[PDB]
Image (cartoon, rainbow, N blue to C red):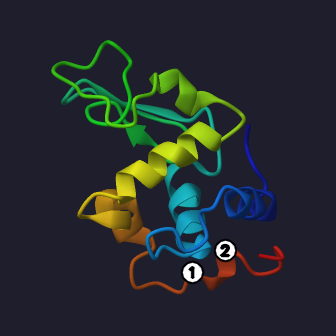
Amino acid sequence: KVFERCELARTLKRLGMDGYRGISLANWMCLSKWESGYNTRATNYNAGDRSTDYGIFQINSRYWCNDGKTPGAVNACHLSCSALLQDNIADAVACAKRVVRDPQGIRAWVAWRNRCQNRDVRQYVQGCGV
């Protein structure tokens, strides 16, 4: 599924993402936008280390989910990577929350540092009723 902007904002809000570990909804929106264009079936294979990024948040298989084909990988979210390719984003959100409970927080995603950190992300939730 490819979410429309405000649809996703409300979806994330209902799932408890607004202010989760100090991360605003606007930050999660900026993350989703730059990682997958709000597309839940987005995937990216990394030929260098044989890992794959899955879903709307592009969560990597080396540490967060199991796809059975990533060398020496772990599964911190205790989910099949397939769970991160669903139209319903509840499991992806549970996993994203798990990611940010770690030291780095929202900085875990390099794309957030590149396109969201120290940027004006207000535009991502304006008009969505969140």
From the viewer's perspective, is 110 left or right of 34?
left
Res. 70 mark: none
The residue that disc 1 covers is 121
Q: Nearer the viewer, residue 122 or 77?
A: 77
Where residue 110 appears, as percent x and y from the top left, is: 32, 59
* Residue that numbered label 2 is attached to: 124
Q: Badge 1 local density, few (<14 within 10 Å), some, or many (20+)?
A: some
Q: Is residue 128 above or below residue 120?
A: above
Instruction: Name which residue lies at 24% across and 23% down.
Output: 50
Decide: is 4 above or below 40. Answer: below
Q: Is residue 56 visible?
A: no
Mark-to-mark CA distance, 1 and 2: 6 Å
Tag 1: residue type? Val
Q: Quadrant of the N terminus?
A: top right
Looking at the image, do the residues carrying marks 1 and 2 touch, with CB atoms under 8 Å apart?
yes
Residue furthest top in the image: 68
Q: Quadrant of residue 32?
A: bottom right
Taking the spot 60% from the left edge, 74% from the top edge, the residue there is: 26
Q: Position of residue 30 (x, y in %)?
A: 55, 67
What residue lies at 37% left-to-right and 51% top-to-bottom?
99
Q: Name the element at disc 2.
A: helix
> Which residue is drawn at the image coordinates 54% and 37% (left, top)?
55
Indicate the secondary structure of the residue bearing disc 1.
loop
